[PDB]
Length: 458
Length: 6
Image (cartoon, rainbow over all chains, first blue to last red; front, side, top):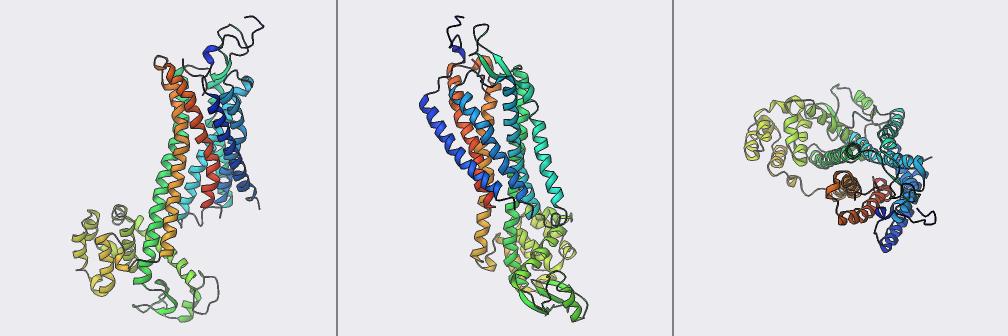
């Protein structure tokens, strides 16, 4: 009415958020937009010049698109001027489509980034030969393609709507879901589960598995470098064979030139019968996963290996390294004792075996490891290598913590929007929801500035 | 009054 009143009967759409909080959120938003712009750009710019950056570069793009596309509009029509929507029906359908499609791309990348890491650390014989530049290329194109398909429902759920008390007005046009609560409910759930819960489970599970493998590699390194011995020259095995390094069986052929011949199909130089320390650990890392694979494809060794902690797994690998998959699987009562976590019982029975009599000094160190779950029988260890272990664990935790700290309140807010029915919305829940809106999204935007810092420390 | 901003 009036045609002379601009702010008409739109009182039911008003939001009572203070201008002081608006100033604070805008300042917080300006800080996040500045850091996130440079951080994601520098990561994206320096990339254009080991395919683990293709995922990092993909993540660096999606975080930047969130700051450039969704942040300005939200700062105007969702923070400062809640109504009316100043971008039309096409803008209403387009904004919520892109904001969700890019949110998927970030969440799916964060998951896919840790998937490649899991395939790089926990499985060295399935990735070194199977991943190509072409596979990783299209794998990322599928991430963006699936993210755009999952955001298609937003083109139908959202839309322009006039909620002014007057039949017609301009100040009543709002960008709100144009479907019933049941349809809004289903759309928000599938969105919430797919992005939030799929990564959160995939991120936290795979990262926990990565932390154990890295701890095993730190434990198995010193245990075998002490018992098996590190020798940079060719020496004769106890059984009369040619070995080198950390017990790298070269060949059973008695020809020394043939042993020198095979000694460098893996090393890559001519050497003339000598290798370096860094080369020995490369042969060691290959010989370790071979023992790990035989343990995993064995049904008599895997249940024991799974129930053991990181330290006791190294003791098992220590035994598999010396005797083989069959020789260790010959132990059948002790493995069941190790499976029941009866350490003192298993420690005594192994002291009866032939393997304990052949190498008494080493067997006690392996047995003592099964007793205490610590490597104290091998000393304190190398502090330089063991600290890099502690670094990577906290980084894996940071990736999990940042994803939940930044995106849990965001999805929780949208659940409030559709699950609190009409009868439960008091005046306080309305004002809280809009103050709650500022906090959840500032945390959501923070991931666009935090990720270029975390994932560039990996 | 349910909110309209998602």
